[PDB]
Length: 130
Image 1 (cartoon, rainbow, N blue to C red):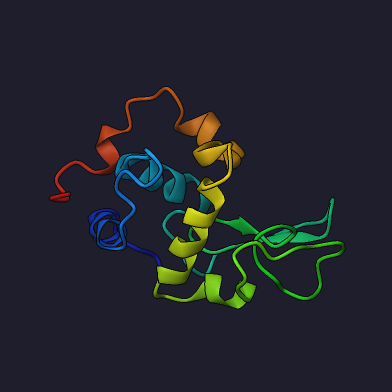
Image 2 (cartoon, rainbow, N blue to C red):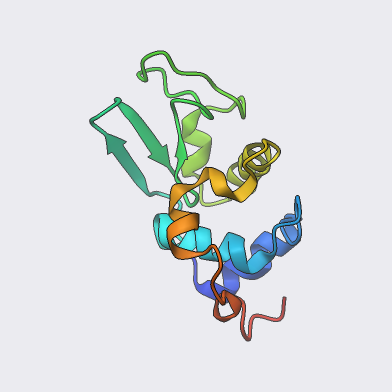
């Protein structure tokens, strides 16, 4: 599904994302926005290394989820990449949390750096009651 902004903000908050590993909700919202456009069905194949980004946070199969067809891949969230395509984002969120428990934190996503780091990300949560 394609989440409405504030719908997603409250959904992420209820799943314990606000301030997870020191990351505010507005950052997570900025990430989901630029990665998938708040789209859980979003997938992007990477011809260069034969891996695929899945779901709202576009998590990569080469490292975080298992899709069976990615060469020399690992499964750090221990989930089928299919779980990253559900309308219910609890699995995607548990995986995003696993991702940020690594040193890089939110910086794991290159896109967050380009579009979110050092920017006023207030607008992502404005009026959502979070």
